[PDB]
Length: 269
Length: 15
Length: 17
Length: 15
Ligand SMILES: Nc1ncnc2c1ncn2[C@@H]1O[C@H](COP(=O)(O)OP(=O)(O)OP(=O)(O)OC(=O)CC[C@@H](N)C(=O)O)[C@@H](O)[C@@H]1O
Ligand SMILES: [Mg+2]
Image (cartoon, rainbow over all chains, first blue to last red; front, side, top):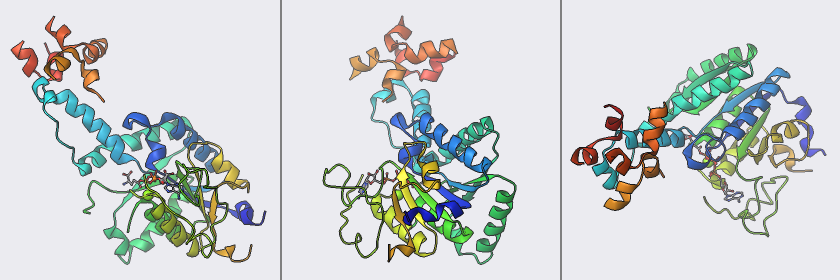
């Protein structure tokens, strides 16, 4: 169809993986999903694309790691006592290292180099930063590398989510497609549990904005949508699709109808 | 809870 | 390693025994 | 047993 017609001209891609995709049951890494996504990204990078990956899920992985360590270091007497909460910043600082080590190992198995770029909120207001980041990203992509962006949570003092960061980077680096990998198959007219909700294949701002009732479950579908609209009307089309399927990325890149599209040229389609 | 813990194992204190 | 696994699974009572 | 109830699991690992 005319909707998925820009896919053949796609050259630079920004892919975001949520917490519901990176970390599965028990707070541990979801090895199957992450491996499939990494294999798809390596195939894409070998086929001539510039892939940018914006990861997440460091908080949960670090929280699980610190809970084990706390259990190991504790005392039977204390195990009895309700154990206190763990600091969120400490959990993020622990989990980022493990997540990046896993990413490096998986991409080394496939012979792909990765780079870790950590940017906070205060950095995006400097005049020079928005210029130097573009040059660094371009230099990395020219050399066939996959930058792995995230929000440095250990340092940051705190709307901005990981999805807003993804939209921001899509705008700045002039990407040509933005894919949001989440748990649900895509944006629905209502909560996915209800049987009266159907998968929308095109988000027209003057038709679905008022007819969509968001539920709940860093940000639900009330913030993914905001970031998607922001990125799309800045000029970068947006695709939302489930991260469970491994082959959704390639099917999107082949022009097949997958997920919901945020495109500015949806006024007349 | 005491007897429970005395019976449980470290891994069991997990989850 | 095997020792670690054994501890991780041993019941406090067994550590007693 | 008092030692065993006040020990930390790691401690059990070290003789
Ligand atoms: N109308 C609807 N249609 C479809 N689905 C809907 C709808 N209404 C509700 N839902 C449900 O909405 C949920 C959204 O999922 P969600 O909120 O869990 O988003 P998700 O991507 O998984 O996590 P995140 O990226 O936001 O977390 C981070 O950014 C971490 C940042 C970083 N510092 C780190 O700590 O790593 C879906 O699941 C459910 O269908
Ligand atoms: Mg969110």
